[PDB]
Image (tube, rainbow, N blue to C red; front, side):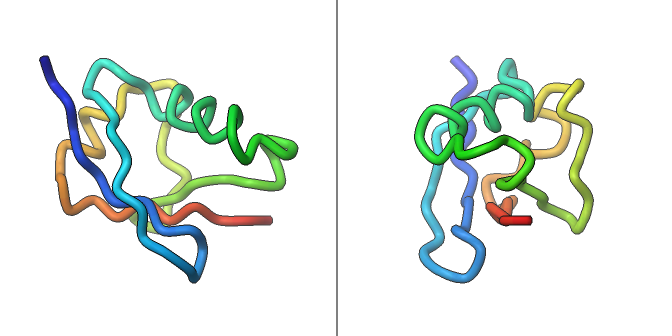
Length: 75
């Protein structure tokens, strides 16, 4: 019952709104992208506040903000 609507921008392109949860970890967010854009999970990597965040921890702690614009980055 905790659907967090965050904004994820494709590096420089479109800012897409993603349906995540507080029960979901950042690792699971990566895994979602891994299902679509999963081309080597070390070539694509998402970072928000300039940090890679702790994918060990749930997205609730960092992504609680619906304005949290996570940038889908490419290495």
